[PDB]
Image (spheres, coloured by chain):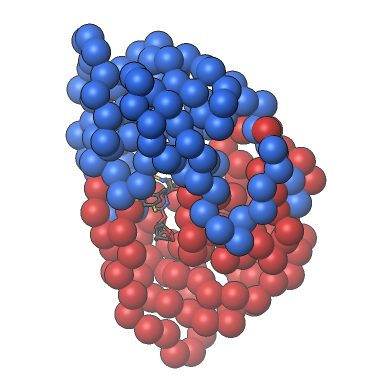
Chain colours: A blue, B red
Amino acid sequence: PQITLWKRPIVTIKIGGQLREALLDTGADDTVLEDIDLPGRWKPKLIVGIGGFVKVRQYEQVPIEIAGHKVVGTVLIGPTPSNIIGRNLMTQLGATLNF
Amino acid sequence: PQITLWKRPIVTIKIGGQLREALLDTGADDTVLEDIDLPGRWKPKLIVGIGGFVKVRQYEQVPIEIAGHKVVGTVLIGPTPSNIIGRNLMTQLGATLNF
Ligand SMILES: CC(C)CN(C[C@@H](O)[C@H](Cc1cc(F)cc(F)c1)NC(=O)O[C@H]1[C@H]2CO[C@H]3OC[C@@H]1[C@H]3C2)S(=O)(=O)c1ccc2nc(NC3CC3)sc2c1
Ligand SMILES: [Cl-]
């Protein structure tokens, strides 16, 4: 799909059998989700945003569906005001910005 | 132009006669720049990112050139780890996400 930016670019995701919404975020290198259970091992990671840092769990090779597209990639789980899909997963969709 | 997302989507801006780089940031409602002098009156504003909040200066009806395109809009000045162009200005470029 093509979307304009008058509204927040929010898409449906399915991850670990959980349905959520998340923002397609070209300003995010990595994908950060708050509200999710993932199985198995993870690595501590500190990430830096506007207004400081948060501690997240890095989960690797997580299967995730973004607006119908199945991809596998790194997901960070931790406090974020908004679930965000980063460039790590949007590149797997072949996503582009046009102006 | 069209750009892919394997790299950060960085563009050149000109604002208040000052040249800078900034991220085209679909996850940002508003535009936030750190390294800038703007003339005249402004309003206190608190904005929330990953890792918390920052106090910014809201400047209204600021002229800004983004990859060649002259627009006028609201600019927030304050601490951000990366200059970000938000949807408030990307809608003026007719920017779209495609996948
Ligand atoms: C600031 C950017 C440069 C980085 N961020 C992405 C932005 O898109 C956020 C998204 C977001 C939207 C929200 F709704 C709420 C939020 F908390 C966050 N936008 C934002 O904060 O916008 C602000 C301001 C703009 O206007 C308004 O709109 C919303 C608010 C408000 C004020 S990030 O989240 O810090 C980020 C993400 C992944 C990541 N991966 C990394 N990789 C590792 C280092 C190797 S570093 C890294 C950093
Ligand atoms: Cl690129």
Tell me where residue A6 appears, x and y as whole percent.
61, 61
Image quarter of the N terminus of chain A: top right
In front: B83, or B6?
B6
Question: Is there any visible trace of residue A27 in the rendered image?
Answer: no
Answer with the quarter of the image where residue A96 lies.
Answer: top right
Residue at 36 percent of width and 47 percent of height: A82
In front: B62, or B4?
B4
Tell me where residue A86 appears, x and y as whole percent.
48, 34
Tell me where residue B4 appears, x and y as whole percent.
68, 33
Extreme residue toward the bottom, this view: B41
Question: Is there any visible trace of residue B52 in the rendered image?
Answer: yes
Image position of A55 with respect to B29: above or below: above
Residue at 37 percent of width and 66 percent of height: B78
Answer with the quarter of the image where residue B47 lies.
Answer: bottom left
A65 left or right of B94 in image: left
Image position of A22 with respect to B66: above or below: above
Residue at 61 percent of width and 42 percent of height: B9
Tell me where residue B69 appears, x and y as whole percent.
75, 64
A83 left or right of B19 in image: left
Answer with the quarter of the image where residue B86 lies.
Answer: bottom right
Q: Count all numbered tags in the image, as a single digit.
A: 0
Image position of B83 with respect to A49: above or below: below
